[PDB]
Amino acid sequence: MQYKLILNGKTLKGETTTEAVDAATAEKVFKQYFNDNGVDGEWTYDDATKTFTVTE
Amino acid sequence: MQYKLILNGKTLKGETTTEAVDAATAEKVFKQYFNDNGVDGEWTYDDATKTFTVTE
Image (cartoon, rainbow over all chains, first blue to last red; front, top):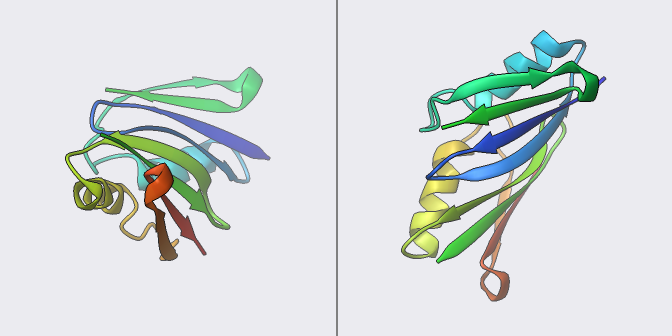
């Protein structure tokens, strides 16, 4: 299944997309790129659209 | 000035944006977020659109 990530920050902003077995594997992939580069933000998720949102 | 990044690959795809002093600082921010993440892709830049592109 396709999953999506929305990135909200002050140093950087963006949007990304991946395919994983489930929402926790896509959450694990998105956390590999987006945990401690500088963002260190608050996570949110909407299952009805398979989308994650990360906010500084 | 605003700079941009485009990500092409097999584990993640996407687009991101930053505001930096020069193309070298925008390249440094984008290389801090996109250092490896198992992509390890080829890097390209077009100055006429202030945009960087990364491909597997």
